[PDB]
Image (spheres, coloured by chain):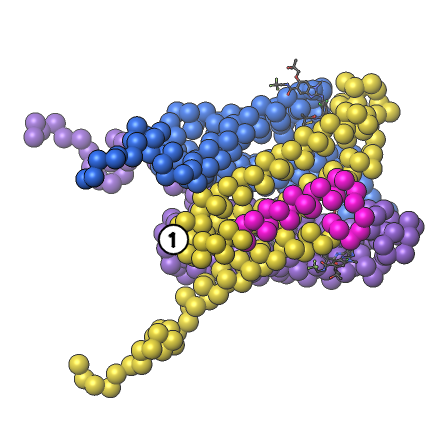
Chain colours: A purple, B blue, C yellow
Amino acid sequence: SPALPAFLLCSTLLVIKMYVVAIITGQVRLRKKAFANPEDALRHGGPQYCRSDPDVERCLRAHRNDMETIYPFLFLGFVYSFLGPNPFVAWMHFLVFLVGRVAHTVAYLGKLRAPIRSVTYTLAQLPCASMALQILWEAARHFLPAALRAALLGRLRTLRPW
Amino acid sequence: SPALPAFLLCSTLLVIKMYVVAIITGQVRLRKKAFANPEDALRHGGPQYCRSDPDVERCLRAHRNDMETIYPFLFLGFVYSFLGPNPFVAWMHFLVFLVGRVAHTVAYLGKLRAPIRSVTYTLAQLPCASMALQILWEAARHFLPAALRAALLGRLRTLRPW
Amino acid sequence: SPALPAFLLCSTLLVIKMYVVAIITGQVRLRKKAFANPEDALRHGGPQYCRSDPDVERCLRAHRNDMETIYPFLFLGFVYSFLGPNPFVAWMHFLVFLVGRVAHTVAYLGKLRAPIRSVTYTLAQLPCASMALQILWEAARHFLPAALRAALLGRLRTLRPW
Ligand SMILES: Cn1c(Nc2c(Cl)ccc(CNC(=O)C(C)(C)C)c2Cl)nc2cc(C(=O)NCC(F)(F)F)c(OCC(C)(C)O)cc21
Ligand SMILES: Cn1c(Nc2c(Cl)ccc(CNC(=O)C(C)(C)C)c2Cl)nc2cc(C(=O)NCC(F)(F)F)c(OCC(C)(C)O)cc21
Ligand SMILES: Cn1c(Nc2c(Cl)ccc(CNC(=O)C(C)(C)C)c2Cl)nc2cc(C(=O)NCC(F)(F)F)c(OCC(C)(C)O)cc21
Ligand SMILES: N[C@@H](CCC(=O)N[C@@H](CS)C(=O)NCC(=O)O)C(=O)O
Ligand SMILES: N[C@@H](CCC(=O)N[C@@H](CS)C(=O)NCC(=O)O)C(=O)O
Ligand SMILES: N[C@@H](CCC(=O)N[C@@H](CS)C(=O)NCC(=O)O)C(=O)O
C-alpha cells in the first residue's frame, strides 16, 4: 500500500492542526477572560469571567467543523489506502483535503469574507465523497452474484461436461 | 474477514448519512436566514441574520449525536470484523446499528413524539455495547496467565520428564 | 504487534467511559428536568422543561472534550501499535492517556478546583503528541531519497563495477 505513508502523513498533520486549534482556543480564553466553568473563572480573576466570547465561540465552531470532517477522513482515507488506488491519484485526494482543511481553518479564525470558508469546505469534501463512493463500489461488488462477477471478467458458465 | 465488506458497507453509508445531515444543516441556515458568523450574514442579507434558529440548533444536535455514536462504531465495528465473528451475527450487529441510526435521525429532524428518538438511540447502542464487550473479552484473555489459558484448552502441565 | 491488545484494551475502556458520560448526561436531564427538545419536555412534565441547565451543559462539555481527544487517540494509538514500539513504552503511552482522561472526566463532572482539570488534559495529551511525532517520523523517512536512507544504514554507493 504505497498510498499508506502518504495518508499517514496528511492525516497526522491534520490531527496536529486540530491540536493547534485547541491550543488557540485556550489562549483566546485566557486573553479574553472568557471561561466555560466557574472554577476556571475564579482562578483567573473571578466569577464575572465565567462568560462567553465571540472569538471563543468561533474557535469552538472551527474545532467542531474539523471534527465533522477530519474524523471521517481518518476512516475513509485509511480504507481507501488499501484499495490499491493509483498512487498519484491517492496523493491528490489527500493533498486536496489537507490544503482545503488548512484553508478552512485560516478562513474561519481569520474571519475572511463569505463565502471563502464555505467554498473551502466544499472543495475539501470532494475527495472524501470520491473515496466514499469508491469504497462503496468495492464493498458492493463483493456481494454481487458469482455468475455476474464472472461475466464481468469475460467468463460465462460452460455447458461442456469437463 | 467475511464481515469486513459488510462493515465497510454499513459504515460508509453512515458517514454519507452524516454528510447529508451537514447539507441539510446548511440549507436550513439559508432558508431560515440563521447564520453563525457575521461574515456569512452580510453575504446573505445583513447583520440581523447572524442569529440562532430552533431548526438549525436541532440539526446541530442531530449531527453531534451522530458524532457521539457513529464514530466509536467506525472503530469498534472495524476491530470486531477481525475477531472472526459469525458472519450472520456480524451482519445483524451492523444492520441494527445502521437502521437504528437512520431511524434516530428521522425521529430527530422529523420531530416525532417522545420517546421515539430516545428508543432508537438505545436500540442502536445495543450492538455497539456487544462489540465493545467482545473486544474487551478478547483483549483480556490475551493477558491471562499461560497456565490458565492452557487449562481452558484442556491442557494441564505434565510432571512426566519428556 | 504485542502493543495491539494493550491498545485495544485501553481504547475500548475509553469508548465505554464515553458511553457512561452519555448515560450520566441523560440522567442529569431527567433529574433536573432540562431537555433540549420540546417533544422530550412534553413527555416529562411540559413545555417549561425545554430549557438549559448548568450540569447538563457541563456534561456536554465533558463529552465534547472526550470527542476532541479520545477519537484522535483511537487513530494515533492504532497506527502507533504497528510501528513496533517497545512494549513497555507503548503500555506507558496507553496508560498515561487512559488514567489522564478518566481523571479529566472526574475533575470535570466533579467540579474540582482549577487548574486540576486543565492539568489532566495536558498530561493526557503528552503521549498523543509523542505518538503523532513518531508516526510522522516514520512516514517522513519513507519519502527520503534512497541514497540518503542507504547512507543512514552505512551503505554508500560503489564505484566498483560489480
Ligand atoms: C493555571 N493553569 C491553567 N489555567 C487554565 C484554566 Cl483554569 C482554564 C482554561 C485554560 C486554557 N487552556 C489552555 O490554554 C490549554 C493549554 C490547557 C489548552 C487555562 Cl490555561 N491551565 C494550566 C495548565 C498547567 C499545565 O498543564 N502545566 C503543565 C503540566 F500539566 F504538565 F504540569 C498549569 O501548570 C502550572 C504548573 C506550575 C502546575 O506547572 C497551570 C495551569
Ligand atoms: C454564496 N455561497 C455560500 N453561502 C453560504 C454561507 Cl456564506 C454560509 C453558509 C452556507 C450554508 N452551507 C451550505 O449549504 C453547504 C452546501 C456549504 C453545506 C452557505 Cl450556502 N456557500 C457557497 C458555496 C459555494 C461553493 O461551494 N461552490 C462550489 C465550489 F466550491 F466548488 F466552487 C459557492 O460557489 C458559487 C461559485 C460561483 C463560486 O461556484 C457559493 C456559496
Ligand atoms: C420515557 N423514555 C425516555 N425519556 C427520555 C427523553 Cl424523552 C429524553 C431524554 C432522556 C434521557 N436519556 C437517557 O437517560 C438515555 C438512557 C436514553 C441516555 C429520556 Cl430518558 N427515554 C426512554 C427510553 C426507553 C428505552 O430505551 N427503552 C428500552 C428499549 F429501547 F430497548 F426499548 C423507554 O422505554 C420504555 C419502554 C416501555 C418502551 O421499554 C422509555 C423512555
Ligand atoms: N455544522 C455545519 C454544517 C454545514 C457546514 O459544514 N458548513 C460549512 C461551510 S458553510 C462550515 O464551514 N460551517 C461552519 C461551522 O460548522 O461552524 C453548520 O452548522 O454550518
Ligand atoms: N448528548 C446526549 C447524551 C444522551 C443521549 O445521547 N441521548 C439520546 C437519547 S435521549 C439523544 O437522542 N440525545 C439527543 C441529543 O444528543 O441532542 C444528550 O445531551 O442527550
Ligand atoms: N474546547 C476546549 C479547547 C481547549 C481544551 O481542550 N482545554 C481543556 C483544558 S482547559 C479543557 O478541559 N477544556 C474544557 C472543555 O473543553 O470544556 C475549550 O474550549 O477549552
Q: Quadrant of the N terminus of chain A?
A: bottom left
Return the x and y of residue C19 as percentages of the image width and height: 62, 34
Return the x and y of residue A64 as percentages of the image width and height: 68, 48
**Rendered image quadrant of residue B121:** top right
Return the x and y of residue B41 as percentages of the image width and height: 79, 50
Q: Is the CB of mark 1 within 8 Å of ligand 2?
A: no
Q: Which residue is nearer to you in this view: A3 or B84?
A: B84
Report whether residue A77 is seen. no
Return the x and y of residue C6 as percentages of the image width and height: 48, 45
Residue at (75%, 51%) from the top-left corner?
A: C116
Q: Main secondary structure of the magenta part?
A: helix
Q: Which residue is nearer to you in this view: B9 or A50?
A: A50
Question: Local crowd at mark 1 within 10 Å, few (<14), some, or many (≥20)?
Answer: some
Report whether residue C2 is seen. yes
B140 lies above or below B92: below
Bounds of the magenta segment: C93-117
Q: Is residue C88 left or right of residue C155?
A: right
Residue at (44%, 57%) from the top-left corner?
A: C86
Q: Amino acid at mark 1?
A: Pro
Q: Quadrant of the C terminus of chain A?
A: top left
What element does badge 1 sit on? Answer: loop
Q: Is residue C22 left or right of residue C3?
A: right
Residue at (71%, 41%) from the top-left corner?
A: C106
Q: Is residue B71 left or right of residue B43?
A: left
Does residue C104 show up magenta in the picture?
A: yes
Q: Which residue corresponds to mark 1?
A: A85
Residue at (68%, 52%) from the top-left corner?
A: C121
